[PDB]
Image (cartoon, rainbow, N blue to C red; front, side, top):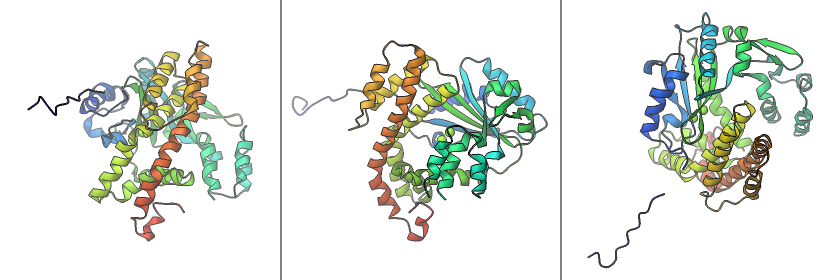
Length: 367
Ligand SMILES: [Mg+2]
Ligand SMILES: [Mg+2]
């Protein structure tokens, strides 16, 4: 009888959560506008979104366009595409990546580190870091990443060339006609905020597998070298890929238990990207900061003085300074969130690393 121990309780409760509805929407409304060959058989979703992780972060997709699109017409096709995107107020193309500036390639030999520090500016930053003697090389590549890997804004593509370090110019056509893939970094509104969609155009018949190995191996190093115990779980997720029970626990820990931590870090990064790439209005910038401040309140036991400063910066001012200050504080906040999640994750990391044969530890862990 419900006269007695009856309670009700319900009661309901935000940020982007995966739903088959969302996937259907990007596949039918967005993909036809951002891919070079839309065609279910010509593209493939990868990464977190292919995994339907509940706290959605990004959509990574590959478009295999060869031979319809090859080096013969890749320039004309990309130009057509950028023009279309620039005409679409609903879709932002932050950056198009293609090519390298080999003057920033590594392969070691101290001569060349000096020979390539010095094409820079705050390059004492480079040297200040030389003071760390290997893994030195890892944080050097970290520093010169955007010099070495060519990122083009739409404007640079359309003008057809851009200026590099030391009054060197690079030409966009030569670049694409002597390359094999292009990375298109888009932002599209899905949540109540912009989400990045990454499209890789493969216009030769190249095996991308080596690129997967190295990105995986890259994430490993990046996580381990900076002792980020949260991210250090990602290799383990791949390692136990075939143990059903461990896979579910790692997936839970990474995607559900601490999913929001990861999502807030991406969202903050997306802010910095939209900013630096010149596509961030104060309306958009403010909406994003709002949702972030909201969701920060749901990280149990999380505290930060940064929250306060972000609060005051919101006050009048010019959009210009508001956006700049926010950006600066969001960097601190990113680190606070990184540290919070990394501390909570240390136990799980060690708990699961200890579960891998000591021989294989070398390949899932860095001393
Ligand atoms: Mg992904
Ligand atoms: Mg991605």
